[PDB]
Image (cartoon, rainbow over all chains, first blue to last red; front, side):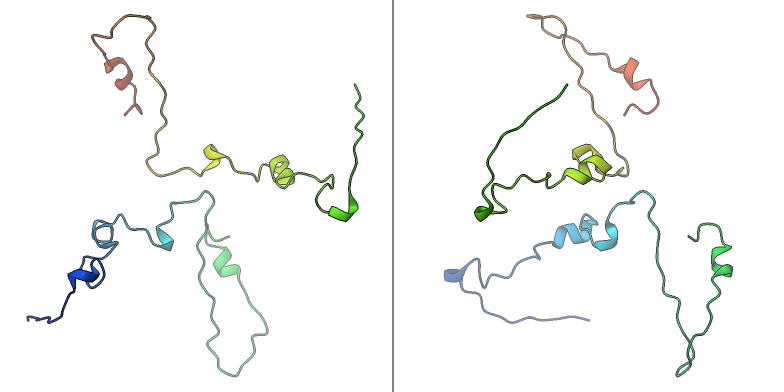
Length: 75
Length: 75
């Protein structure tokens, strides 16, 4: 595969209309850049996941959490 | 021991000139209030302490760190 790019730049507006690397390009590539879940480990942190309904049009009348809570580390 | 306080308060400027509790008062007393060293444990964190000179007007000609770096956990 290959690409070609054709465009104009205007030095008289520089740095605007200049073709540049991304503001965060290097930190993105090095793994320095942080996202939401890159927050360090907090003491007593837990993780969440949804419990879902699978029966369209039905109503949930009873929920048994015991099989989940029997696993050590489920809170 | 005992104290007395005498002061004016100006209802027309309220809440300016009102005698109130501190903005942070309850969190300061509960231990919810955070100061610089209440920042959570960070991964790979170390603690610093100063090594000090004890001989005024002398020059330090040699530093032997090996007795310190011999202790596990000194980096």
